[PDB]
Image (cartoon, rainbow, N blue to C red):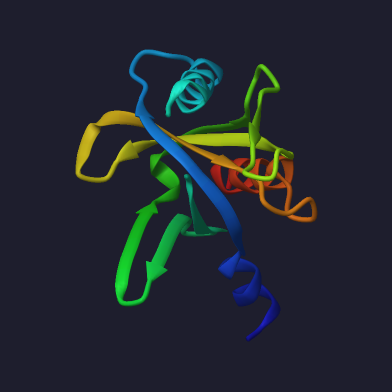
Length: 140
């Protein structure tokens, strides 16, 4: 586990997975805003493991032997930001969490642009930092 290899492995943490919505012909900020509107208008979100690395974004969740996984390669990711209206997610305890999303091509419907929306769980792995890391691996 050398420095450069570790650093390529990137950072992973837990986040709430709020929703995913198709977002064609919208700017990046419009896409994230659209997703947040949908999430905030709907009638409990899953906690997922969220990894950002040189290889892109990987989302996973397991309950016993049931398993969810999606990977978004770096060339597929077109945008990420916190909610441009500064809207927050209200947790079951009534406290609020910052919202962020990214837009990527849908792996099995590649013509489709889809915004994946999340809320922060840890102030020490905050939404703004995750957005910074995604934008860095896009920049690379």
